[PDB]
Amino acid sequence: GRARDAILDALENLSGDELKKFKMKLLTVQLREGYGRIPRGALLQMDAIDLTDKLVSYYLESYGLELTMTVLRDMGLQELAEQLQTTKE
Amino acid sequence: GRARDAILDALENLSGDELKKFKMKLLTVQLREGYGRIPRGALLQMDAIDLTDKLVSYYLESYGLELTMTVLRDMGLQELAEQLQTTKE
Amino acid sequence: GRARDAILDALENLSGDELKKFKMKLLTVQLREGYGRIPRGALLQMDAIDLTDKLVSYYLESYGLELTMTVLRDMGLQELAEQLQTTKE
Amino acid sequence: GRARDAILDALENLSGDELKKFKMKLLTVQLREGYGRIPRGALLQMDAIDLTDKLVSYYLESYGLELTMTVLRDMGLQELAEQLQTTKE
Amino acid sequence: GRARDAILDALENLSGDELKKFKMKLLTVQLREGYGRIPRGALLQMDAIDLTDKLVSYYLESYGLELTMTVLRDMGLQELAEQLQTTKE
Amino acid sequence: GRARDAILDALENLSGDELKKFKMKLLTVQLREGYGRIPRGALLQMDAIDLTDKLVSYYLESYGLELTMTVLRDMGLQELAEQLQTTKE
Amino acid sequence: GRARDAILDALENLSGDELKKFKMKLLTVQLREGYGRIPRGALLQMDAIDLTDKLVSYYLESYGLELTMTVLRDMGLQELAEQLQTTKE
Amino acid sequence: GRARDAILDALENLSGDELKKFKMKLLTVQLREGYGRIPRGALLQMDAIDLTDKLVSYYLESYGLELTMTVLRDMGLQELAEQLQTTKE
Amino acid sequence: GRARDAILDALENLSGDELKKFKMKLLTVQLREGYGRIPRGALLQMDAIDLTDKLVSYYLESYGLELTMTVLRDMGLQELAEQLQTTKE
Amino acid sequence: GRARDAILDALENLSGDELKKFKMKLLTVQLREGYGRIPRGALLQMDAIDLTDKLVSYYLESYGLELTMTVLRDMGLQELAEQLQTTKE
Amino acid sequence: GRARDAILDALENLSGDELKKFKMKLLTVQLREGYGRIPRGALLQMDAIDLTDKLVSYYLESYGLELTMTVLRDMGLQELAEQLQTTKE
Amino acid sequence: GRARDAILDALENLSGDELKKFKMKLLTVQLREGYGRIPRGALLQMDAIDLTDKLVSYYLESYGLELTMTVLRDMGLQELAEQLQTTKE
Amino acid sequence: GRARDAILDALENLSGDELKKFKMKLLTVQLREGYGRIPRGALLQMDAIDLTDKLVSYYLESYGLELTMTVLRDMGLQELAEQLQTTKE
Amino acid sequence: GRARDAILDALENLSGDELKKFKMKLLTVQLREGYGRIPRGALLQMDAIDLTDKLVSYYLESYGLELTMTVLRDMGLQELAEQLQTTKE
Amino acid sequence: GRARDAILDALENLSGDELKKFKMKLLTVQLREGYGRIPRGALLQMDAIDLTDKLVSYYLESYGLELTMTVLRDMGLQELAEQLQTTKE
């Protein structure tokens, strides 16, 4: 599924500081019922590449891909949000 | 019964750390009446391949196969849970 | 009586360690009245094939065959228990 | 006993540094009479998951579960202390 | 006597390391007068299942069963100690 | 029949871990009707060289040789599968 | 086949971080039909040298060698991609 | 003799690294005449529990118990030295 | 002994820079005879929490607790020195 | 003569490895004149119980009993040496 | 033949990591016709000392000694290559 | 005929594992017409010394001696093959 | 060879930043034919002391020593270049 | 010989970085004739305590003790060099 | 002859790894004419104690004792070499 690769390419375009903000905010974001939550301990020491694999692991590609955008806009509208959306099509 | 082979292929796709979590959680999972429980001593030193053979040995293929998924989701929804479910059909 | 051959084929499918557990447990299992008990000395040094002949020798084929399953399940439900039961029919 | 699973889920939400503080403090915490103390050697190299199994092993689920909270608050009042308490009910 | 089977089931739930501690400690435990002591040579190479048969062989079921618990608590209070006690009733 | 020697030379080129996977998978592989199945007890403790002699003993050289490849590919396509096939010619 | 040695020499010229990216991306890369996929568990803990032997083991030298380049360019055009291509001739 | 058990309980409270220092230093410690020295080969691979049994085996309980403290202080004054001394009384 | 916990709570209230000054000065501080000195190698890489456990390990709680204050004042009179003294009472 | 029984009880308390050392050393030990030496061939395959009967057979109980201790201490001072000596009185 | 000893002394001067590289590369190195190839299974678990004995076992001392250097230089020119060559004279 | 003694001296220089390989391979080796084949049953339980006497018994010294080398090289070129050949002269 | 020690003493007199420049430039420097090139992966994470041992390992002391100066001047004429040259004499 | 203990106490007072420098320099230090050299492979992974035992093992206490100082001064004059010298007297 | 006992006591003071090196090197050591060589097969599986008896069996005590030292120094000068030499006097 190219989906895994798509997220990876974009996510890596964020600066070090914002990254923390993203990971941290993800912990407090609301998710659809029937899914689990990622343990705090792992998230704090995880890497950008690693985060990619795990992120998809918990959520399906289709639903998982959409969930990402929801958080990106939350931190403010980024060109990335739309850039990534193009992949959805 | 391809069932034995199906579980094997998927179970092997888990990382070393999660494996412990799976085996350990299995010990505390609730099972249907009329079945036995696996001894703690063996589980602690068993291998992934070995675990496959024994797992089916105690539980029937049909019921045994379903029991696995119940635990996989418990550790959180994994793509594996659904991937394996496809085999059920 | 194919019964002797049926038990033999299945019993041989057990691992070396479990075998001890089976033989040893047999000594403490409850039996119907009117039958004898097998001497401890012989059981400790007996072989899997030999055990087959002697096992039937003390108990009748019909009753002897059923007695085996009772012990197999006791060590936990094994696919063997049901597999062997099919022979009963 | 879901109790084992409840502790596990929460305990894993602590950061790596605090973990040491928790384990280390546990060694100096006062316990009710009639119970043993965990050996220092094992505690120093134990893992979060492993710690879960052993922790319950020494103390009963009911008493063991309550003992955990006593230590959590000691390190300061954490949302976890109350979150876990909900499980008590 | 189900007593032999009861001990067996529980004793097997101990990890490999603790097992040594149990066997070794048994050698230095105080016993009621009128009974013998088990030879060191055999104990060092004996197995968990074998240990079960011999353990009861030297001590009567009633007294033998109680003696076990005395040692289990000594290594610290284990859920096993109480779990096994239930069998006493 | 050089066939016995051919298999031997190649089979020995597998690592210790994969070996288990091969032997274990062989137990669940489908075989042509009119042939027997190898007892689980022996397979678990057999050696690589010994396995060679017995493997051919149950199945004819021609059919036996082909059966091996079927399993090798199953564990994934290995250079061995083709390397051994050359011997077929 | 010098092919095994050629890959080895070049692959070792990658920095530690990129290595992860390569291994991880390999898992999601599309492969020609008739071949297997490498288990996630092994890939995560494998070494650069070890990866070399296994990589060729699953895929033939000719096809295997070409597959590598396809992934190298994917991570971006590297001098290595062309440098290695020279070996193809 | 509770002496054997007393040493065991305390000795186990040392960290893995210090343990080596203790065992190694024991080899160079001066002992009273009329006693033997423990072979280097065994000491290097011995375990903490095992070391307990053997330690007492060579030296009498009374003299053996005192000898231990002499070495503990040597590695520096430890709370253990005094804690164990209490047992002497 | 709450003493271990008391020191811990206060010691942690020092800034990163002063910490070095404290540890380093401890190496050159005069101690009462009959006690050992802590190895330089360990002190340089030790942590604040770890330092707590070891600090008490070498010196008794009563004497160890007093020794700390002696050094705190040396680096200058701190509110901590008196704050900690209150614990002495 | 209880002497035969006394030796037997103690000798059996030695581990398998030390046993070899004892038997082997006995061959090179110096004996009082007027007595014979035991053939190497028999000693190598003899058992612990058997060794007891033969040991006394060659040497008188009084002198034979003392000779044993001489060798026990040689392998180092064992609690057994003194324990057995008590029997002398 | 001092040749066996010469290789041993030098080969042992390689670091753990390079060792793997050497053994692994040996498998793909070209050898003169009329000689056999060493089985992969043994090479993977062999030791440095053991490797010495076996290495000479397959190849004659004269030819075997020269073959080693050919591989050493391949991994790059090492002082060892020349140091060992001196032995040739 | 020193021939019998020559083979014996060399054959005994093989490790336990290779021995099996030799005996087993001998069963599948091609022999000149006019000679018999050794029964499988005896070969499996025979000893190295015994094998020497029987080996010569079936084949003449001259032809028998040459036949041995043919098999030694087959398992790969060994120094033994040539060492033994010297005896031929 | 004091040569190894000579380089070490001087190389350590370079500032952290220049060090990178040196190591990096070494990768692109031209070397005499018949020698190998050092892998990029190792160079990036190597230390100043370690670099010393390896640097000499690939190149002979005489030629290796001269090669160093060639690079030092390249980064500009340093007092070190001449200082080290004195060692050549 | 207190000599072994003396070295140990001082050697442990060196920081982690200098330790490497010491071990590495030892490899290139000149030694008196009639003695051996320590293998590079072991030195690289050895520990400070272990190094103590082995260091004395190769060189006599008297000569071995003096050899240490020679290297300590080489890395520069340290208070340790003189501190240790006091032990010589 | 105390000689047998002297060697035994010292030889046992070697670590497991060095032991292999000693036994293996013994096979390639040069011996005085008029003596035999020990078979490789036995040496590989022999024990330290057993090796003692056999070692003396082939060589006379006087000459045999001296031969040992020659090999000990070869593996490097050990304190053992001299320690054992004292016995010669």
Image: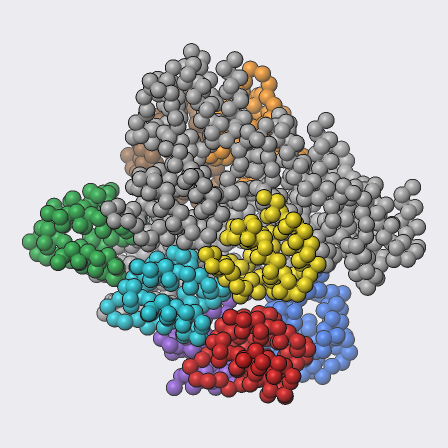
Chain colours: D yellow, F orange, H cyan, I red, J green, L brown, M blue, N purple
In terms of depth relative to the viewer, which is nearer, H71 or F54? H71
Query: In which quadrant will I find the N terminus of chain H?
Result: bottom left
Rendered position, I65 above or below D17:
below
Q: Position of residue L12 (x, y in %)?
A: 35, 41
**From where the camera sits, is residue M53 visible?**
yes
Residue at 74%, 75% in the rendered image: M18
In terms of depth relative to the viewer, which is nearer, H72 or H24? H72
**From where the camera sits, is residue F66 visible?**
no
- Left or right: N41 in relation to H26: right
In terms of depth relative to the viewer, which is nearer, H21 or J5? J5
Rendered position, M56 above or below J51:
below
Residue at 28%, 34% in the rendered image: L1
Quarter-of-image position of residue M28:
bottom right
- Left or right: J78 in relation to L10: left
In terms of depth relative to the viewer, which is nearer, I41 or F31? I41
Residue at 65%, 49% in the rendered image: D89
Q: Position of residue H75 (x, y in %)?
A: 43, 73
Quarter-of-image position of residue F86:
top right
- Left or right: F14 in relation to J33: right
The count of marks equals 0
Q: Position of residue I53 (x, y in %)?
A: 54, 70
Query: In which quadrant will I find the C terminus of chain H?
Result: bottom left
Rendered position, N85 above or below D2:
below
Q: Position of residue D85 (x, y in %)?
A: 66, 53
Quarter-of-image position of residue H30:
bottom left
- Left or right: F47 in relation to J25: right
Residue at 29%, 52% in the rendered image: J18
